[PDB]
Image: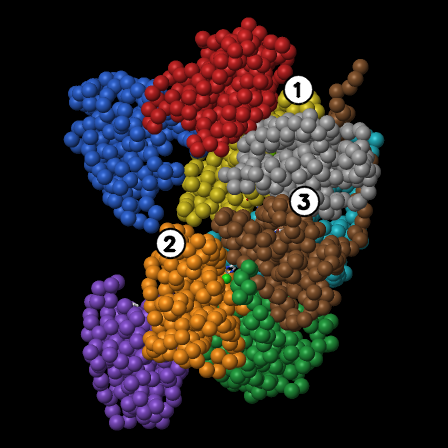
Chain colours: A green, B orange, C purple, D cyan, E red, F blue, G brown, H yellow
Amino acid sequence: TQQPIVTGTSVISMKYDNGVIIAADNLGSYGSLLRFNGVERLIPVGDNTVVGISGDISDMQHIERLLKDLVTENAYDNPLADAEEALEPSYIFEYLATVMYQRRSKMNPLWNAIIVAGVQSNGDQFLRYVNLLGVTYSSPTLATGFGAHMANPLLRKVVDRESDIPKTTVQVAEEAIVNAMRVLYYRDARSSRNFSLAIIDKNTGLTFKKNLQVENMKWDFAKDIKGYGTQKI
Amino acid sequence: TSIMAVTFKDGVILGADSRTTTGAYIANRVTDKLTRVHDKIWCCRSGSAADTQAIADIVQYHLELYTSQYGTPSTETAASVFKELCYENKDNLTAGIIVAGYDDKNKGEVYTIPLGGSVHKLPYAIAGSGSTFIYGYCDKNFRENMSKEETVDFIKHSLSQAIKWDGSSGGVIRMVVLTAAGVERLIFYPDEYEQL
Amino acid sequence: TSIMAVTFKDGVILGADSRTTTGAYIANRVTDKLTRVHDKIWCCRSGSAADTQAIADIVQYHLELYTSQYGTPSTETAASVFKELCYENKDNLTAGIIVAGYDDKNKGEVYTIPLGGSVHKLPYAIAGSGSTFIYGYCDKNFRENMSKEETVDFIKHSLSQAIKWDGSSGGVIRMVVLTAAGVERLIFYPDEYEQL
Amino acid sequence: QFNPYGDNGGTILGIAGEDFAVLAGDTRNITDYSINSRYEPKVFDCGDNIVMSANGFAADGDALVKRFKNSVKWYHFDHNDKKLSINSAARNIQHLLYGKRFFPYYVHTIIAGLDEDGKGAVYSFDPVGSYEREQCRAGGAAASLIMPFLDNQVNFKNQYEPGTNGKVKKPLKYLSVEEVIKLVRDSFTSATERHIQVGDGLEILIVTKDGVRKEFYELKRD
Amino acid sequence: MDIILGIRVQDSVILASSKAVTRGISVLKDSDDKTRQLSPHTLMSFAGEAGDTVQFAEYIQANIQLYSIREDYELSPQAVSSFVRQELAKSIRSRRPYQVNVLIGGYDKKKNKPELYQIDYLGTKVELPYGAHGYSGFYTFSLLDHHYRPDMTTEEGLDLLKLCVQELEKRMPMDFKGVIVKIVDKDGIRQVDDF
Amino acid sequence: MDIILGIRVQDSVILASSKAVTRGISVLKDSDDKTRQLSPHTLMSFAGEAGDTVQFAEYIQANIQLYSIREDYELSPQAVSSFVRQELAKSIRSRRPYQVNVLIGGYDKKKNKPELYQIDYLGTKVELPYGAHGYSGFYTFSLLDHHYRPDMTTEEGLDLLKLCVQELEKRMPMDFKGVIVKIVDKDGIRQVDDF
Amino acid sequence: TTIVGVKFNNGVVIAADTRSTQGPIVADKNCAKLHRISPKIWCAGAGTAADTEAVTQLIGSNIELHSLYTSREPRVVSALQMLKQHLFKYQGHIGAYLIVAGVDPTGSHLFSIHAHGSTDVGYYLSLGSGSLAAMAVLESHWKQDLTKEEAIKLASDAIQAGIWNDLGSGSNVDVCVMEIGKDAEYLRNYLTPNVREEKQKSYKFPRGTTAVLKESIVNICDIQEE
Amino acid sequence: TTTLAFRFQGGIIVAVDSRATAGNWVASQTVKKVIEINPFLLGTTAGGAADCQFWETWLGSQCRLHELREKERISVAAASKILSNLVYQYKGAGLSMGTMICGYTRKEGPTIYYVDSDGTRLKGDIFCVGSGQTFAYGVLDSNYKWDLSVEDALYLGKRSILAAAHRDAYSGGSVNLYHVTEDGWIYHGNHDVGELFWKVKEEEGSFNNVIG
Amino acid sequence: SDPSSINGGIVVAMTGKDCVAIACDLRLGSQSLGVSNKFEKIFHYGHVFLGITGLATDVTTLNEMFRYKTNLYKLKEERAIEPETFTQLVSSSLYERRFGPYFVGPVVAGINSKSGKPFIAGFDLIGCIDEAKDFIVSGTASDQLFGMCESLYEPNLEPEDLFETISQALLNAADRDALSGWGAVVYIIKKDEVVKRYLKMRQD
Ligand SMILES: *[B]([O])([O])[C]([C][C]([C])[C])[N]C(=O)[C]([C]C1=[C][C]=[C][C]=[C]1)[N]C(=O)C1=[C]N=[C][C]=N1
Ligand SMILES: *[B]([O])([O])[C]([C][C]([C])[C])[N]C(=O)[C]([C]C1=[C][C]=[C][C]=[C]1)[N]C(=O)C1=[C]N=[C][C]=N1
Ligand SMILES: *[B]([O])([O])[C]([C][C]([C])[C])[N]C(=O)[C]([C]C1=[C][C]=[C][C]=[C]1)[N]C(=O)C1=[C]N=[C][C]=N1
Ligand SMILES: *[B]([O])([O])[C]([C][C]([C])[C])[N]C(=O)[C]([C]C1=[C][C]=[C][C]=[C]1)[N]C(=O)C1=[C]N=[C][C]=N1
Ligand SMILES: [Cl-]
Ligand SMILES: [Cl-]
Ligand SMILES: [Mg+2]
Ligand SMILES: [Mg+2]
Ligand SMILES: [Mg+2]
Ligand SMILES: [Mg+2]
Ligand SMILES: [Mg+2]
């Protein structure tokens, strides 16, 4: 048992017709102090999987090393390491899910919430969640922390059920993700303007976007707000 | 919360962020923490929103009744009424208030009233959770008898940094200018102050 | 405690105050918080004195044994050994360590390791209780590729303010300069840095 | 302090017929006041004509089901591909659950299938492995809402025959698969109305001598 | 204190109450009468926290005696039980509540019927054919459920009461030093001196 | 369990132990023998936490019986008491200590003397003319301080023991359901069937 | 609970879901969370149901007496001031979280109130367990110079986000529109997107199914003549 | 839970209720609180359902292994002591068990041992165990004799459980009756309290308090 | 410890076609100990019926309080109180004890004498009004009652049909609750006749 020290906030994601999108901001908070402003919380594994991690950053870096080591180990005595016997999103997730549940069972958890986003060999979209308790679930949209409360409602308006996935394009899906990231910046006190976004498409492959910013913000109406009730000036 | 009041040549300027939080949720991103207790006596509020509002409302009532009987009150008098409420009810209040006002005789004055209910007259004052991150900056950059434009830049740069590092601070930077000329409200948006 | 490490054109400079406290009593006013784990790999220590000493002693042992087998270790390698100790023993340790070193290939590098045992490579880093009061100042005043004299002034001014506001920080300002030229120790006394 | 347990909500329902058995469960998965998924399968085909669901803390639920599926696999390896009977599966699950007596799987387990005489069977477990064969059982969050309804409408409890006035009970006539599915759907619709952790979807697994069939129905999403 | 029992038969109410008073590890007394006559045809037994029991009982006694003098009339058992309940219901939300449980056995001279009321310290009133407070009922109610009949005589009621006390003396850990038995009927209140 | 007494007279040791076994609000048994014969001339009575008492007593019994067979010789009461004390002294610093208090009454055939040892669960041993565990001694020691003479007969010891039990039955709150009395002398161990 | 308030061109609109819960159980499926303080001052309430009702009735009662005393139509700032001072005095123990809106001779107004007595001003506001879901919608679709039709749509959509995504909210959407120079229109059950489907079976029992012991007529009438 | 067992002329009567609860929630009315260890040994369950049922089911395996090894059925004393020694190892860990081990052998005759999770092991003639044990004791003690007919002893056991089922909130459902003799145990049916109460009330003239 | 579940008990109310029904169990206990099987929880003031679950001392106290208040109402108003008005009186009376509440779950049932409209309502311990069209539930088996009512109930049931529905809802809910049962009473209420029926149920 411990407590999280340096922490990362929401990771948000959704499925679309040809793949999956995942995003997370670049902040490493130290309680109320916004300590580290250049933290990458989306970690790609091969060219078909992106693991988005929130919560304790020291445990994130540990998980990052496990995944790095997993790729190395998979390549050993494996002539088809870059083909038929490459790491799948489902393999990577199940491994993490096993570790998370084992660690919680020893009363020494990895203090994280994780979303594994990717595309399988047969082109099927993969999107599944796991956290410090070893709890797992899948959904057309997935989000951690504040994202669960604010991003999911917005993303579910685009893809409300399974049958909405083929009707959703990559442009519409990315637009929804970017809007959600803006809303989180308005309302989450442990978020930053800077974020990373990753698209895993079955046709165009893995597109990893860094140094994105929240833009088109509405603040002008603030000038008209005066006092807390009766004050006019 | 990041709040400050700075005296300068022509008077005094109050400054504040606009963030109200319930834990990590931002309950209000466009809050007005610069509140009026008299024509040219204002205050910056930090701590409990309910407490500081209740206090400010009572002070405004006291100074309105003071004015009807004895004419315009001094900034020191306003600070004393704040103090009396904060000190005597210290067990039940969480309020960090900066009182700032402009007289013609005394010019610009700033009084800070921290948690205990003590009073401290200062050339400038900083308070709130975000103030911790700008003690170094403000101490190095403050000068007495600055111009209006210099004081605005000083507050803008200071609160920008406080906002940058403090999770409980954010939104727009509100400012209120108190001089002989009158009362001027200023606002500065994220796109402006973040690139500083 | 107020500690910092700053990379610059010719390499890296470590800086620290000299105060050790048991509550409000200053147990040591001339403490050396800048400690050597290898010829040109040093660290700044904050938190528990016992913990950070024990950690530093173990790291020095590991790097001495590394050197005997594989030659001079990189600054990244030294940071990794610190991390391994801090991360795996996080439940039992209170250590905030900044690792700074000079290679010829990589030049000046700074790695900060906060309480959790995470690693962060940065152009410069600040830590300890007193660092809170200079986030604003340091962020506004830091530039990349500064000169030796500029970097010394930056650290001197920064730690001066941290000392001024933090009760747990004080005494002399110690500094260690890491360049190709070698290792230089600097000291600055209260009469010098207080008047800044 | 770290709390190793959580509550993922949901509700399950097993009903044993004369030559069939059903195991139903909603597809909603939650934490506190948030929905994790509107469709997260909770009832599983474990092989050998046995269906299983472990409702409560989903991590323990998944772990238990995974370990039982494993037990079925090794039962085949060790005993010449012999079919694991429902009674033998139930006893095996008791030992899986009681094995963690002092750090329990925080779940209410129900299995369903056919006994060795071909008759419908439902077995029900508590978290630490106490079990019992039953004709009827609801489990999980809305179990307190559903069970009384099943006592009334499956076992005809407190029902008597008109004209006699409390003297002659209503006879315990058997229920068809079509009749049972109606009671399952009404049970979950009623539970969805008054329980916030129940909704989204209903997935029913029907077990007969022919095998395992599935049926899905929509539930209210509020 | 410990055990108080009550049984309403055909023409009377019988109250049985233990004689022991224990403080800590010592039985200070073995002849204590845990009851007060509220009126000629109304008896109240009591058990609860030390001091509160007697203080409450005597306070109620004084109030009913005051009513009797003022009106030159005896209140019905039902009326007395309602008064007692209100006092306890008032008490439970006081600064320091009366920690007292009572049985009220009375003979209503108007209706010519015996009546037994069980009231706990919360002000929970019930009229019963037989009653008990504390751990007594855990033993005695099963016996009374089996044997009790509504037309029993007073002598049959005493025999059934002896069977209750015998069971308590066999299975209860505490030595309650026997019971004082009192009968309430049309002729008033009397004590059974040999039990 | 509750009350265990011991008295060493001229030519014998007498142990008296209550018969009651109580769990919660029920006396489950009223004929329980809280003792074990360790050897032909050594008897041990016991009281403490449920389960631990019998488990400890039988464990000691087995060890002394093993010694007897191996050496074809009976250990002295002093030797047995020292063995028992060491086991309890070992136990008190264990993961889960034996929560058991014992009296050891034996007749030393070598010295031709009766001997009574009182040992508590901590491993505190004392040789005494009379002893008790629990709240028993709070009553019985004053009586024994007055009446006990060292040259008493076995019959006088039993009469003095009856006076102890009578006092306990008068003043103790718990009904311990009488005592089983056993005498240890040169001829061995025997039970007084009428007490 | 999901409650929202949205300002528009010539007035203000408030909305609310209709679910009340005790733990994980739904106590009431069609609860009324929009309260009338005065004819043109309405407020939505979240938190403890008895408190939101009681505090609204009390202030509404005093507002009515104040209106009669002054011969003036009541103002939203008066209701706001009376509510906050009452709630502050009780130090958050009166669990009322309110969105107060209305029109008066000064104009149209929108405020929020929290249990400890703090007030906030805004063009759009949301309170309750579903406030995060609702605020996500408001932050995504709100703009300046909304029409009446657009504001109702935005307000109801914000409630729906709470209904579908928050387990503490559900059932129906209630709305109240307060436009300047007009009567306030209270739209009870404006939307009904959660009607229960037909049951598979009728559970009407045969008469005589239940076992009875005794029967008797109950005298509800008074004591009779003659 | 209410369970009892008593020795008499015709062997042993064992009677138990059927209710299981989780707080105020009635989890089951059809629980088998008697466990058939072998054709001559019975065990009763009170306290934790899993604890009792796991370890008494386990006890049967140990008893079967004994008679395989020793070519002789296990004594009631030895069977009861296997269980008491087992739970004693777990003492402090939080097992919750109150059990009677009931049987007949040639050397012992009819024997009952009370075994519980604190490590208590007691031989006796009469035992009642569970939350409703006091209610059962009332009926049993007032009506018990050694010279009871199998028929009358069975009814007394049935009636004692009924008494407890009525008054104890955590007892009820139905009554399971067993009769243990020289030639083994004999099941005597499940008796629903909902029907048994009214039957006994009418025939016996008892429960005059209740209206029917 | 929990005041609302020391004594146990339940109340349920339902509307039908030109009729209402209110029913309750008869148990009063002290936790596990069953004390009384005649503790009725339904009372009436004129034609307005009130069921109360929860702490038994408060059940009795509130009955006496509302009898007190409805009697004064009648003397001053010169007419019997109506269900709608009585509901407000219950709410007012409970809320005045906001920070020292009666630990009860009241349920009002009746027919308005002027309009003829069936009316039911439920409350929490501090006064909040739940005015349902279909049914109201209260007590230690409220979860069970919700499940029974939500499945068994259908609108516009005739008085004699409504009796069967509410009776089965109560009985089967009570049988899954340890602190409820020990007998039951059902009131069938029409505009100018009221029938009271005691139900035969299992006594454990
Ligand atoms: B600021 O953060 O101090 C701010 C100033 C206030 C006058 C608007 N205070 C708050 O946001 C407080 C919490 C708090 C945060 C940090 C330090 C001290 C206090 N919030 C509230 O009072 C609040 C939050 N949600 C609803 C109502 N009130
Ligand atoms: B500094 O204040 O962090 C300092 C750095 C240390 C490496 C010399 N630490 C201390 O002075 C600590 C206490 C402390 C103060 C502030 C923050 C964190 C910790 N002191 C000691 O470890 C200490 C004090 N007296 C004797 C021995 N050790
Ligand atoms: B909402 O969730 O805020 C809603 C709004 C209310 C005004 C109808 N609140 C409730 O449903 C509250 C939740 C709550 C539960 C327990 C303590 C405090 C608040 N429910 C009730 O007020 C409630 C519950 N059961 C019966 C009556 N009222
Ligand atoms: B009985 O009441 O002891 C009973 C016997 C058991 C074999 C079913 N135990 C229980 O009902 C216990 C709770 C309990 C109640 C009263 C006294 C002691 C214990 N319940 C369970 O063991 C249980 C099992 N499965 C589901 C729910 N509860
Ligand atoms: Cl504010
Ligand atoms: Cl040091
Ligand atoms: Mg900020
Ligand atoms: Mg639902
Ligand atoms: Mg009582
Ligand atoms: Mg019941
Ligand atoms: Mg019962």
Q: Is residue C75 visible?
A: no
G179 sits to left or right of E125: right
What secondary structure is found at the residue carrying circle 1?
Answer: loop
Which residue is situated farthest in the top direction here?
E187
The answer to whether the beta carbon of the residue marked 3 is less than 8 Å from any atom of ligand 3 is yes
Circle 3 is placed at which residue position?
Answer: I130
Circle 1 is placed at which residue position?
Answer: H205
Q: Position of residue E41 (x, y in %)?
A: 54, 10
What secondary structure is found at the residue carrying circle 3?
Answer: strand
G154 sits to left or right of H133: right
Q: Nearer the viewer, residue F99 or I26?
A: I26
Residue A122 position by quadrant: bottom right
Identify residue type, mark 2: Glu
Circle 2 is placed at which residue position?
Answer: B84
The answer to whether the beta carbon of the residue marked 2 is less than 8 Å from any atom of ligand 1 is no
Marks 2 and 3 sit apart, C-alpha to C-alpha, by 46 Å
Marks 1 and 2 sit apart, C-alpha to C-alpha, by 80 Å
